[PDB]
Length: 386
Ligand SMILES: COc1ccc(C(=O)NO)cc1NC(=O)c1ccc(-c2ccccc2)cc1
Ligand SMILES: [K+]
Ligand SMILES: [K+]
Ligand SMILES: [Zn+2]
Image 1 (cartoon, rainbow, N blue to C red):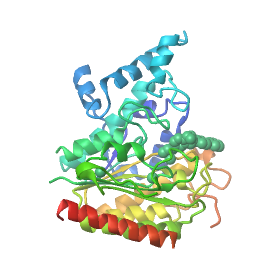
Image 2 (cartoon, rainbow, N blue to C red):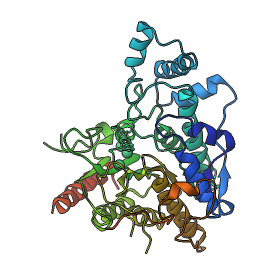
Image 3 (cartoon, rainbow, N blue to C red):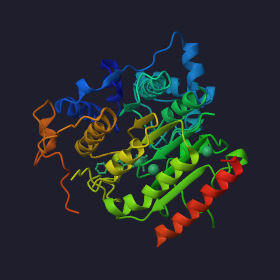
């Protein structure tokens, strides 16, 4: 089936943070308003039988001391008694500050997306679902011992780690505006997890990686050549982004032959995102995201589709509703007819002023990157005997 991760507690926790507020509820209530929910298998988030099991699951990637620091931070924020100098030092040493501050549910909230993405991986492994969607997941910046970019725990690394430890090769495809640095770094030394991030990069722009360093770094040890990056200039539209990524994705699939694909589908590339870096749409006559996802799904590899960035909440929901409907279509083979008009539902008023499903927008560097990447794909294949 097509799985989708949700649940009452999961929804409350994914909506408990100060940065993303109720985005996740808008997403899942828009998916429900368009009657897509009866087509999807509900995947419940994973729960553990003990603190020790939860700890062993999260410290498959993250360090125990970082995990202890994040739990203590939540408890500290469940008081209003502010931090001591020593606790602030401790939090600072894990970048639990500034862009990644504490708040009352920060650990539970962070853990929720891990529980979601680890259940998603399990449903794929156990053959329940061909494709599973977790729009509460996709926190690709978190590191082993460091919060970054409002990612506190890296649910993607953990889910990929569960997939590979089920020769299993995973292709990770990161469509977010921002370089997927935490997932790339986790698998820097790992040939069986090939990472491919397309993103904006430019001087001063978060997080700073995924571009020249001058040449591209692309892995080390047996991981050499297994990390792929396509940084694009600001202002790119659906068709130019589509032509830049499409032959790369296609080559990646032909050569790597992945057992699973993991797709981070962060919506901040939309023309209407407050970033206003990329000019991508959710249009489906074509949306760069719908093109890439449909391509990836035409491969017929079991596939995890995850959320990510997206700071125009109603437009993230318009995009992910369409991704969700496309997936149902490309997997079950049954047409989904979406009204161009948003249906009445609890968040209907958020879709002003037009209440249409389409976002309210009027729409050789790449060839050099293509030859670089195609040569890097050559080295990976010869290095790995494919
Ligand atoms: C630099 O920090 C980041 C770190 C990581 C990410 C991310 O998604 N990575 O994958 C994004 C940001 N940018 C913002 O936080 C941001 C900026 C601006 C807005 C905004 C929202 C509403 C109106 C205007 C601006 C919202 C969020
Ligand atoms: K990206
Ligand atoms: K790798
Ligand atoms: Zn982003």
